[PDB]
Image 1 (cartoon, rainbow over the protein chains, first blue to last red):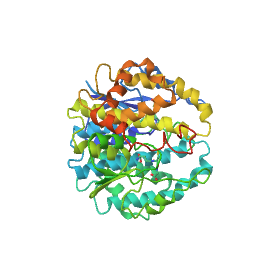
Image 2 (spheres, helix red, strand yellow):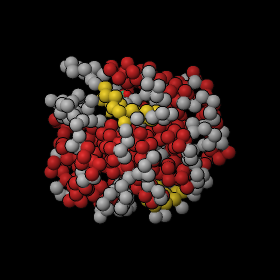
Image 3 (spheres, each protein chain N blue to C red):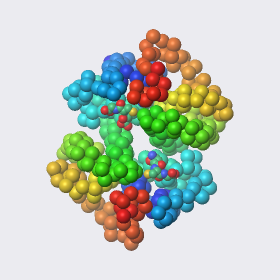
Image 4 (spheres, chains in turn cyan, blue):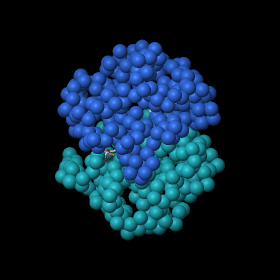
Length: 217
Length: 217
């Protein structure tokens, strides 16, 4: 078995869990929690942070025998690699890295709103810019069933997440982009995935359980 | 002839320059520039932005014949892959993913405060939290000449710019870490790297944007 670990919330560990299901990987989730006090105490992780014995302690993490991986991307590539879910040619590879990185910056932009207290006043900013960075993805993807081509790679697990996050934030965001919304319906079509969305284990409390009224409240 | 492209000021494209020079790649730097504070006008690029045919207009970028690339890491990996500067074994594979993504984090940490309005107030914090980061690296190298092992790869280049940038903020920061020092010495003393260092083609303005009152010159 393997061991993944993150906060009781969504966070980065999401796609990571999704990629772990598509590969039938037998993993376990050491879930850490933030103290429900007005001020959320994050010292639960801290207590173990250094005892796990990780090269660069941080959450999320994945331990596997003689392999304790850290850094969201570093964890995904590891799994994907063991299941041929990575690009094979320079071509599919340049697309792969561009996306891999891009989606991250994009993951940040949305996350910023939540990290910043003055969300409500700054929320519009992200909303107005959305379409531009959206059409870019829908154009790059184009007529492809999966972002890279006719084969599914780890990069889709990243994609889907960054696209669902914007979908729950604002549902109309994808209506003008048929292929993008269609992309999501295809992802949420994989047996191994659909089945997972019908599992006994999913959020006990709402999304963003801790931090940001964008879920916390 | 490949095509690079970034603001006149050093920025983050320092690693690509070094790698390109270490790999003897013929390249033409299409240097851009902005206006002065407060009007930080960056028109030249702004207009040119989309006509370049970049599927994801962003800076920096590299136009390699057909392969037009964006995203720092992507550009680095491309070149690094062209001349075999990468990890082969799963140990080297997993190793480079960790560091590559980690250094990016640290690189995001430093700049975030130089671009920050209260730099003169955040400064002592990063100082106090520098040794943690800096030790983590020294522990992840030990007696190895290169982070990956016995091969210089793009990681060592990316690790150089960061360790270099941090050795500016506080020149003594890495003094308590002897191997980190020998590393910097090691990189700087490479047949081709040295030649580039002491050239007439090494003159972009210092550490990041002029907005930041951090080593502007």
